[PDB]
Image (tube, rainbow over all chains, first blue to last red; front, side, top):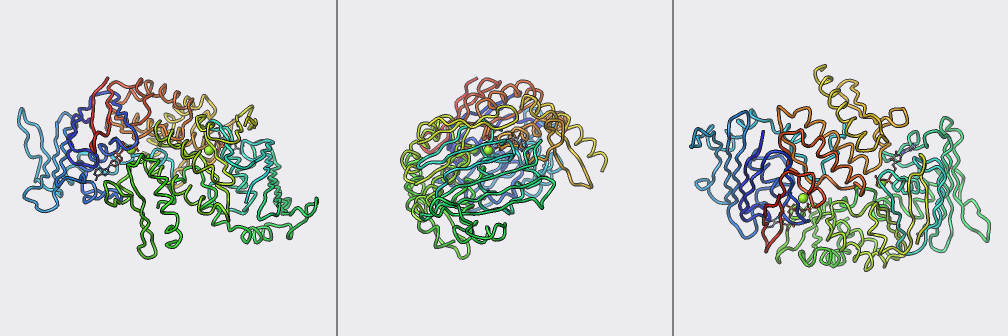
Length: 149
Length: 148
Length: 142
Length: 145
Ligand SMILES: Nc1ncnc2c1ncn2[C@@H]1O[C@H](COP(=O)(O)OP(=O)(O)OP(=O)(O)O)[C@@H](O)[C@H]1O
Ligand SMILES: Nc1ncnc2c1ncn2[C@@H]1O[C@H](COP(=O)(O)OP(=O)(O)OP(=O)(O)O)[C@@H](O)[C@H]1O
Ligand SMILES: [Mg+2]
Ligand SMILES: [Mg+2]
C-alpha cells in the first residue's frame, strides 16, 4: 500500500487540508496542538470507518463550527489506484458519501456498492484492519505496545 | 512526609549509592539507562515491600553479579524521624532482614516487630500505600493515569 | 473519588490555563455516578478529554498532579515525578519550567527525575547520575 | 504454528541488529521465544538473556522502535508502508541523534514511511518535509523539503 494524497475537511483542527505524500521518508513537523495526529486519524477513519476505537467518535471529530466532515483518500495497492471518499453529516444520508473506486484511465469507477458495509468488506480483503493497526499505523503512545506479549 | 537519605546497594544498576534529599525541588538528571527510575523504585521497595507491581521482582532486581540487596531509608513524618532497612539475599530468602525504627533521642528504636507484615501494617497507618502510588510517586509513563 | 477530584479542579484549571497559554480556559470536574468525568473548556464550551492532543494530555496530567500535591501540601507534602517532559514540544517544555518555579516550588519536597538538562534551571538541588562501569554513579551538583 | 515461528524468528534477527546499533551494543541481541502461542522477548546483556523489565524506560522505547522497523522491513514488499506518530518520547539527546542514524539506514528501505513529530531535528533524515501549524483555529500545511 502507498498513500498518494489526503484531503480532509472539518476534521478536528483541520478545516481544509491537502497533503501529497511521496515515496521515501515523509516527515510532518508540528507543535503540540497543531494537527499532526488529527490528519493521521482521519486517514484511519476514511479507510476503515466504522472503527472500533473508543477514543474516536463521529459526533466528536466534526470540526466545532462545521456541519460536515470530508475525507478523500487516494492510494495505490498492487498497481491499482484506489480512492475512498467519506462525507459525514449529522442529519441525512442523501448527502452522505461513502464510495470506494478504481481508476480506469481518466475516470474513477465504483469498486463496489457505495456504503460503509460494502466498502468495509472490500477494504478488509484488500488490507485487513488488524494488519493496518499493529503493522502499519503506529498511533501516538503505542510504540512499545508491540512488546506487550 | 519528607525523604532525608536513601542508601541503595545492589539494586538494578545501583552498586552502592547514597543520596541526601532536601527541601524544595530536588532534581536528578541522567541519561537513558543511567539509574534514575531504579533509585526511585528502590525507595518504593524500601517503603512498601512487598509490592505487588508486576514489573518489580525480588528475583530480578538484585544487581547482576551480586547477592546482597540493601535498602536503608531515612524520612521524617509529623515531627518523627523514621528509618526502614531491608536486606534481600539472592538464593537465601531465609536471610531477609526488615526493620523500621524511629529516632528517640539519638538512638534508633524499633517501632514494631522486625518483619514485613509488621512494618507494612505500620506504614499503611502512617501513610497508605494507596495514597503513595496515586498522589505521591508518579511512576515513569504514569503522568496521565489520573485522567483515566 | 467523586468528592476528591471536586476539590483540585480550580487549581488544575488555573495551572492548565497557563500551561496552554489560555488555549483552554478551564478544567471541569463533574460527577457521573461511580465514575468522574473531566472536561476542558475550549472556545467557551466544555469538550471531553479526547478533544486534546497527546502533548496537551500530558500537560493536563501534570496540571492535575501539581494541583493534587498542592491541595495536599500540608498533610502529605511530597511529590515524586519520573520524566515529566515526554511528548512536550520545545514551547510546552519552557512553559513547564515556568510552572515549576511557580507551583512546584510551593510543595515542601519534590523529587524530579529527568534526562532533560533544561530542567536544571528551576531546581533547588541538582544531582547527576551516570553509568560508570556497569554501576550507577551519583554526583551532587546543586 | 511453525510458519509464525519462521516469521517471528526472522523479525527478531532484524530487531536484534537495529537494537544493538541503537544501544551501541549495550544489548547484543534480542531473543524471541514461543512456548505454546505465548511469545516472550529477551535482551542479551553481559552474555545472558534478561527479561524486558531489565530495560530502562528509554531503552524500552528504543526496543519498541526496533521491532516496528524490523516488522515493516519483513513486510516491506507486502505492505510497504510505515506510519509513526511521535517516535521520540523518553529518548535522551544521544538516543534521539542515534535514532536519526537508524533512520537513513533502515527507514529508507521501506517503500513509503510517514513520520509525524514535534522534533525539528528529524528534519534531516527526511526526503520530504511538511510543516503543520494551527492558524486561527485551523491547521495550515506548508510544504518545505
Ligand atoms: N472538534 C474539534 N474542532 C476543532 N479543533 C479540535 C477539535 N478536536 C480537537 N481539536 C484541536 O486539535 C488539537 C489536537 O490535534 P492533534 O492531536 O492533531 O495535535 P498534534 O499535532 O498531534 O499535537 P501533539 O504534539 O500534542 O501530539 C487540539 O489542540 C485541539 O484544540
Ligand atoms: N539487575 C540488574 N543488574 C544490573 N544492571 C541492571 C539490572 N536491572 C537493570 N539494570 C540496568 O539499569 C538500567 C535501567 O535503569 P533505570 O530504569 O534506572 O534507568 P533510567 O535512568 O530511568 O533511564 P531512562 O531515561 O531510560 O528512563 C538499564 O539500562 C539496565 O541495563
Ligand atoms: Mg499528536
Ligand atoms: Mg527511567
